[PDB]
View 1 (cartoon, one colour):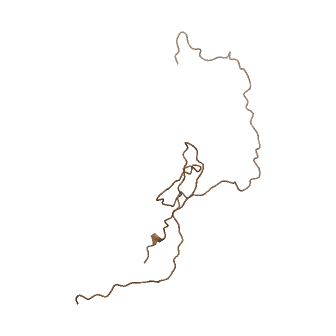
View 2: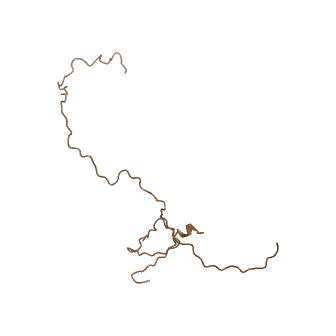
Length: 83
Length: 50
């Protein structure tokens, strides 16, 4: 702010002001609020809580069976070298 | 005395048929998982014309 003498800035907005209204009042709000609809315990989703496999491992079962059977052919006898 | 991996692996040949081809559009036949595909043969039976 600058004040300049001799033209000085009025020393106030004075008493000639026009009170325009008495509408100043905010009427307090008084209220009762009830949000009470029956609630049912459940919601349907496509899927909740699953941690789906991105790849599975290979998996398997097992079997064996049979017996011990055989047809054989042997090497001929040979002269013994030494000993 | 037996090799166990050889006998628990399967070496198979299998065929299938797919349709829905359209000119200039990529027709894709997906490979399944788990299988180790050694070769692929595709025969374009173009409505009886080869």
